[PDB]
Image (cartoon, rainbow, N blue to C red; front, side, top):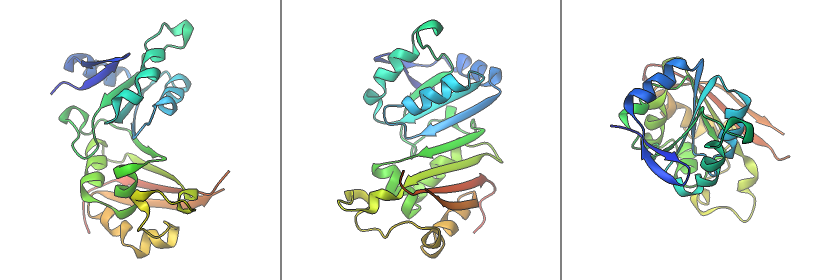
Length: 204
């Protein structure tokens, strides 16, 4: 019920009332699903102190170094608006339901990457669950991963292009789970596939 949040190197139960207070005080709430070492989320947190930047990742021990520098005083690189949550997107806590003004999936790997490419329901629904209505979903995937050697988790999958996003039915599956595709574009450095969706009612 309380979020399992990082406090430096240790894991912590975040006080449900403090969690609500932080959201209210924030002008915008941004959720980074799949953070890695979460230093991208940290840079965002430092760049936008009025934003509540929530980093979500199951591998919480890789975020610890960032969590340490974030826990410091403001004069030494502290980011009190950064919240690193230990969780998978497939099984998100109820405290994370509908909290996001924006959901980002930047350079995913493993199940998150494969889930996004294939359009797995458990992943897409988990992404949808944390978003407020009208919230944008940003997915960024570097297309260099389909060069050899190709990572195992997308090894059997054809390269994701704007045309394949449609032809594979990924767009349909996003639509059936509450995500309305707004834009898809290749951006070259390495080409980066950008997908933009908006949180809506699940149709088909």
